[PDB]
Length: 203
Ligand SMILES: Nc1nc(=O)c2nc(CNc3ccc(C(=O)N[C@@H](CCC(=O)O)C(=O)O)cc3)cnc2[nH]1
Ligand SMILES: *[C@@H]1O[C@H](CO)[C@@H](O[C@@H]2O[C@H](CO)[C@@H](O)[C@H](O)[C@H]2NC(C)=O)[C@H](O)[C@H]1NC(C)=O
Ligand SMILES: [Cl-]
Ligand SMILES: [K+]
Image (tube, rainbow, N blue to C red; front, side, top):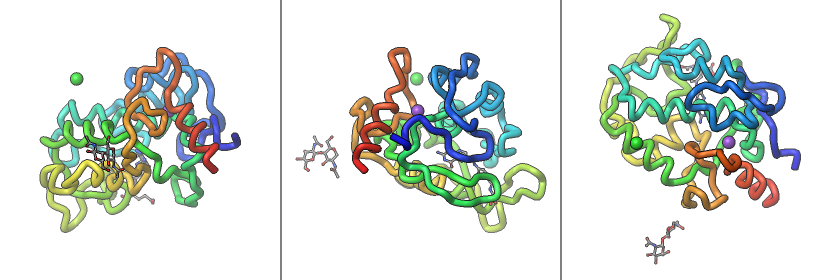
């Protein structure tokens, strides 16, 4: 149970999960229990936020249908109090902990990949390798802009590879209670609580 209802020790996270009534737009489904502040939830909706100075439009403008998924992902990363069982210590300059091999529901990965098909990028790992010397990430030497499909030939390649394995792709369905959903209605409770509960008891 020590892995339940926690916030990892990372760059913006709160020390502990709490109610956040004013979570902005896409993060609001987390408003009953979040690891992010309202300010953070607000900032992550912005192009090239002050959170990480990360530019989504690094190979031209990213399609809205695609960008929403990255915003959604950032909501989960910053707000989720239910990733306890996958938290690992990594000792990095901008975070002492992170999560790895979170069982992301296949349909979520599939939808993300499909909606991002018509967008563009220059790298398959977005955590390491950028040219930051202007202050925001720019394609490094040798990295050409291409379609998403080029750098991520399958859904799993994007979902698992883009954020250096924060996720593994689960063969479980949305609503199985056996995989983490990036996209959920939380009117009747956050569905990923049950997921974290289940995998914490697996030991
Ligand atoms: N699911 C998910 N998992 C994550 O870990 C995650 N992380 C971020 C934060 N993203 C980033 C990406 C790059 C850099 C960055 O400054 N990269 C540098 C190296 C940083 C270092 O010293 O470790 C670079 O090499 O370009 C920081 C934060 C956003 N969404 C996520 N979403
Ligand atoms: C992931 O789940 C799917 C079903 O949602 C599994 O599919 C079935 O697999 C068996 C063989 O193992 C087939 O007889 C069925 O035809 C499959 N169902 C359909 C309609 O596709 C799939 O095997 C699972 N993947 C893994 C690796 O366990
Ligand atoms: Cl839609
Ligand atoms: K969650």
